[PDB]
Amino acid sequence: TSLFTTADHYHTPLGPDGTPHAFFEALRDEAETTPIGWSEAYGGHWVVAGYKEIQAVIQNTKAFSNKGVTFPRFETGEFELMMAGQDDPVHKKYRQLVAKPFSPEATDLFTEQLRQSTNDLIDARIELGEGDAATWLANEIPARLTAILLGLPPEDGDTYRRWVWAITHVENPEEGAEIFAELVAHARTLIAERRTNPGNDIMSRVIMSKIDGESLSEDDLIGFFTILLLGGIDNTARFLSSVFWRLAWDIELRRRLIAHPELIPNAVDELLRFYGPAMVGRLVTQEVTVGDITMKPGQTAMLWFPIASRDRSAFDSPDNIVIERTPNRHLSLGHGIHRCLGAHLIRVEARVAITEFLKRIPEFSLDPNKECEWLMGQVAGMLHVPIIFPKGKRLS
Ligand code: HEM
Ligand SMILES: CC1(C)O[C@]2(C)CC[C@H]1CC2
Ligand SMILES: [Cl-]
């Protein structure tokens, strides 16, 4: 019996703690023998689980194309995910347009405003003694950030969340496509406004940009809007919700972060290794051999980062959250030419969120009368994390 045969990142067995980690640990064990295996799911595809096998695949851009970055393909109609869905040379030119606003110096500019935002969100319920850390905090922090990056109203998070649900999780394709079509309609109006009244945001930036002398098509612009919205509302919210869930029951990890705030950035990196939401696919475009296995053009390889992140040949004690772990070269943010554009920004965001939360609410736990829930998929993590805590005071 192999766990690869029915491996499916949208349908991962959950264990008693509520997470797929027991399943990930079992798959990791098997990957020591078979680091790449065939899955029967989605009509058949390769599941790449070993650390060095994922490295080999992801560096080999000649045989493995980012046209398969989402598998099954995300619902973005006729639009492509910019950067993430392209290969070089096209990929490099698009990414170059937004490197500056994602650079560490550019994104550090938001730290103090992320800190205020986190404290304001906390104020909303600190007096209540209860709340869903996902919906109340983890979702809202990146949504509000992302709205400001894109020059959108920050109070319309429920609209952006609905768009992201359509792209990734609605299963009736009619609803899926239709709601993505609503994103497109909003995106066009914003582009038209920024065209005439340009601002500081990243959208105005790409709208005014040029490649080889020429403006970006409206479709290219919509692709930029789309992938940026996905990074914030989806990946970051799921990551933070898993972190909040962990901090809720893991009283040992929590007291250490409270006592050693200087360890929080390194801890954020270890939490990324352990709770990294993401997997990505690659479309095989050339016959290629990786380890014992020969892949053919047209096949897809799914890079199961959470398994590689637990590889005993790449990490000592991989099943433990070791907050002082260095160098910690996990694959949660990718590697090589497609390496996460928002890497530094999420590190700031997580450091701020954790810092402020533990500062305001040092004592809290999972609500024993409400359920947690894990969202499965290409972006995976806690979706509901009901917590209780002693009633406290607003800063406002
Ligand atoms: C915890 C949060 C996040 C995680 C785990 C994550 C994960 C990843 C991964 C694994 C990749 C590599 C894709 C590949 O190899 O095909 C990637 C790329 C990318 N990410 Fe992130 N991401 C996060 C947040 C964000 C945010 C906040 C943004 C921007 C607002 C963002 C924007 C991008 C873009 C544009 C790419 C494509 C880069 C390229 O193709 O060169 N991500 N991300
Ligand atoms: C799943 C993953 C990693 O997140 C986004 C935002 C970046 C790359 C891919 C697809 C979209
Ligand atoms: Cl290690």
Image (cartoon, helix red, strand yellow):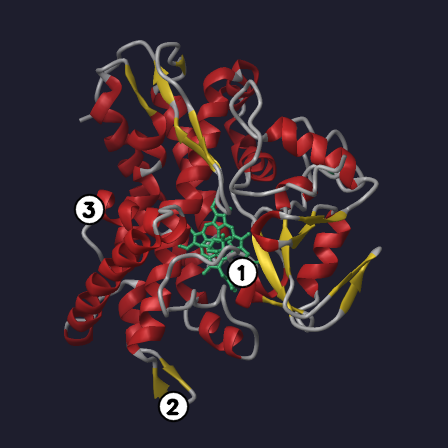
Q: Nearer the viewer, mark 1 or mark 2?
A: 1
| N-terminal label among 1 and 3 | 1
Name the residue nearer the viewer: 263 or 292.
Answer: 292
In the picture, the quarter occupied by the C terminus is top left
Q: CA distance from mark 1 to mark 2?
A: 29 Å
Amino acid type, mark 1? Val
The answer to whether 171 is drawn above or below residue 24 in the figure is below
Q: Which label sits in the foreground, 2 or 3?
A: 3
Q: Counting other residues with Cα less than 10 Å from the Cα at mark 1, is it few (<14), some (14-19), or many (20 or more)?
A: many
* Rendering coords of residue 224 (x, y %): 37, 66
**In the image, what residue type sits under mark 3?**
Asp
Q: Residues within 10 Å of mark 2 (few under 14, many from 20)?
A: few
In whole angstroms, how far apart are the C-alphas of marks 1 and 3? Answer: 28 Å
Q: What residue appears at the point 48 percent right and 38 percent down from the top-left corner?
A: 376
Q: Is residue 326 above or below residue 125?
A: below
Q: Which residue is mark 3?
A: 156
Asked whether the beta carbons under mark 1 and mark 3 sit within 8 Å of each other, the answer is: no
Q: Give the labeled residue for mark 2.
A: 213
Earlier along the polypeptide chain: callout 2 or callout 3? 3
Q: Is residue 313 left or right of residue 87?
A: right
Residue 20: x and y in percent read 57, 30
Residue in the image at 22% along x and 16% along y: 127
Going by the image, does 361 lie left or right of 43?
Answer: left
Instruction: Tell me: 13 left or right of 310.
Output: left
Give the residue furthest to the bottom: 213
Q: Is residue 185 at least partly visible in the picture?
A: yes
Which of these two is toward me, 69 or 360? 69
x 37%, y 62%: residue? 76
Sort mark 3 into few (<14), some (14-19) or many (20+) by Cα contacts within 10 Å. Answer: few
